[PDB]
């Protein structure tokens, strides 16, 4: 048996008026413990490959496997140029004395998505590629 890394809720919306992709990070659930104490200090990292210098982060939530994020993030790119891009939503356990530990991620290849209407999804977290 593989255990699940965690369930993540998020939203995609293309804002045609402002010309931006809106990524909303709503919450996570049943995240994995990456501290010995049996909890984590989760935060999500969000960016739009192949561009990796434009990287956002959520606030860190001390000690919880069911964080409520509630943050929205913007990427200025035209609906047409959104093609070959993949959206990465990377959950991490903040460790103050060392590398922060990867919990898991969701990668959304933007080519495959319907974005006429807005979208709200839950996705299982997968290990890094
Ligand atoms: Ca840790
Ligand atoms: Ca930690
Ligand atoms: Ca660590």
Image (cartoon, helix red, strand yellow):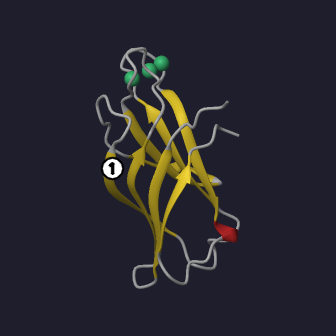
Q: Nearer the viewer, residue 4 or 61?
A: 4
The local crowd at label 1, few if under 14, some if 14 to 19, many if 20 or more residues have their Cα within 10 Å, is many
Quadrant containing the N terminus is top right
x, y percent for residue 67: 34, 42
Q: Residue at x 43, y 44 (%)?
A: 44
Q: Is residue 26 left or right of residue 21?
A: left
Query: Which residue does the image show at 59% across and 32% down from the upper left?
Result: 3
Tell me the residue that label 1 is attached to.
69
- Residue 33 in which image quadrant: top left
Residue drawn at (46%, 83%), measured in percent from left and top? 16
Please provide percent x and percent y for residue 10: 45, 59
Q: Quadrant of residue 5?
A: top right
42 shown above or below 53 = above
Image quadrant where one finds the C terminus: top right
User: In the current view of this chain or complex, which residue is farthest to the front?
Assistant: 1
Compared to 61, does 101 lie above or below? above
Asked whether mark 1 and ligand 2 are closer than 8 Å, the reply comes as no
Secondary structure beneath dot 1 equals strand
Q: Position of residue 55 (x, y in %)?
A: 48, 48
Viewer-proximal residue among 65 and 61: 65
- 16 to 83, vertically: above or below: below
Q: Quadrant of residue 81?
A: bottom right
């Amino acid at each position: 048996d593989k255990h699940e890394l965690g369930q993540l809720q998020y939203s995609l919306d293309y804002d045609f008026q402002s010309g931006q992709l809106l990524v909303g990070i709503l919450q996570a659930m049943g995240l994995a413990a990456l501290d010995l104490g049996g909890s984590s200090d989760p935060y999500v990292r969000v960016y739009l490959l192949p561009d990796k210098r434009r990287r956002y982060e959520t606030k860190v939530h001390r000690q919880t496997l069911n964080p409520h994020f509630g943050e929205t993030f913007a990427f200025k790119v035209p609906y047409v140029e959104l093609g070959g891009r993949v959206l990465v939503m990377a959950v991490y356990d903040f460790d103050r004395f060392g590398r922060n530990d990867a919990i898991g991620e969701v990668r959304v290849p933007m080519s495959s998505v319907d974005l006429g209407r807005p979208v709200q999804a839950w996705r299982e977290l997968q290990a890094a590629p």
